Image: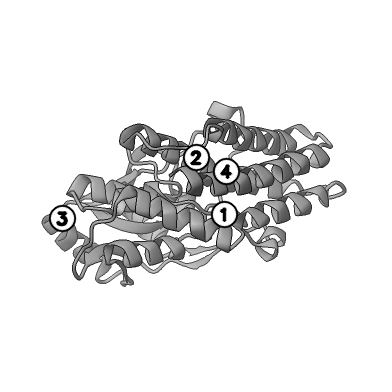
Amino acid sequence: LDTFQGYNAYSSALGEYAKQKNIDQVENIILSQWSFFFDEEQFYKNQWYTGAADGPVDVVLNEDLRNFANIEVLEHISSESQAIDEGRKVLEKHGLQIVLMDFYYMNSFNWKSLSRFNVTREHDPHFAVLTQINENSVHIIDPYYHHEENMSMEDFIKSRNSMTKQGKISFNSYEIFSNGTKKSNIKELLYYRFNRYLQEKMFGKITQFGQVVKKQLDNKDRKWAFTGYNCLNSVVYQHQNLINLQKKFSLEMPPNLQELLDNWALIRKKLFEYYSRGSYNTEEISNLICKVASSEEQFAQEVLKVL
């Protein structure tokens, strides 16, 4: 499908809703995000430990939506007694509901398209958009994986009341609400993001990621590299989103933005190869990560000079 990508499941759902319902500023605030995190504690629990943002909810994006647009994302927790009828009310009034769903019950990404046939099912929280409630069936759009599916009501209820690796889903839904909006110019959004990126030394988190990768040479469990591959899609998306902003707004960018995208895509390729191919190239992957960290630091500084 031709759905809004964002840079993660949460931002993809928020942006898809905003696009369909003509809610101002949300798309531009998502597309102008520039972030990196690394959590060594989450690395060793094999939770989602790196990329653009901790999740499933992107708290930094919510802070940006509040600070720039005075936009609040309200979390509705519900019960099996109320959740579907509240959905009906929301669908009647708005046509769409943003929901938290256990990805175990979704089939959104075809791993066989990348020659991975051992498609392990995991209880991971994921954002989708509910578009239709019938008797014993529902329709949902997964805007992050550009997939739709019809799901039995029984499977939809199970996906929304499931214990996951990140805790219990309890029919959670997300309402985009505004007290009173503000307009932000795209240059202001990028200026704040790049200033914050450098001030919080987010490039330093890329270096930390690189140093932890170097220390996995003797680790026979390669699960971290599959987790990292999935986590870093969010960084590739932020790079592509900034390229799309440059085109749309005819912006001034440092000349190596495409090269940085290419570097992150190669890191992903080598992580996926390490996970699946049994290579002993943690040193090579570490060095690529440590190289892009220096490049991203310089890129952020140059954006602020030219923007």
Q: In this view, does 201 lie to the left or right of 135?
A: right
Residue matched to label 1: 36
Q: Which of marks 4 and 2 is nearer the N terminus?
A: 2
Q: Which residue is farthest front?
A: 305
User: Tag 2: residue type?
Assistant: His
Q: In this view, does 274 lie to the left or right of 90?
A: right
Disc 2 vs disc 3: which is toward the camera? 2
Residue matched to label 2: 239
- In percent of width and height, residue 73 lies at 31, 65
* Residue 299 badge: 4
**Residue 292 in view in this figure:** yes
Q: Earlier in the sequence, mark 3 or mark 4?
A: 3
User: Tag 1: residue type?
Assistant: Phe
Q: Earlier in the sequence, mark 2 or mark 3?
A: 3
> Separation of disc 4 and disc 2 at Cα?
12 Å
With respect to residue 286, does 64 lie above or below?
below
* Residue 94 badge: 3
Q: Quadrant of residue 182?
A: bottom left
- SS state under label 2: helix
User: Tag 4: residue type?
Assistant: Phe
- In percent of width and height, residue 4 lies at 34, 41
Disc 4 vs disc 1: which is toward the camera? 4
How many marks are shown on the rendered structure? 4
User: Tag 3: residue type?
Assistant: His
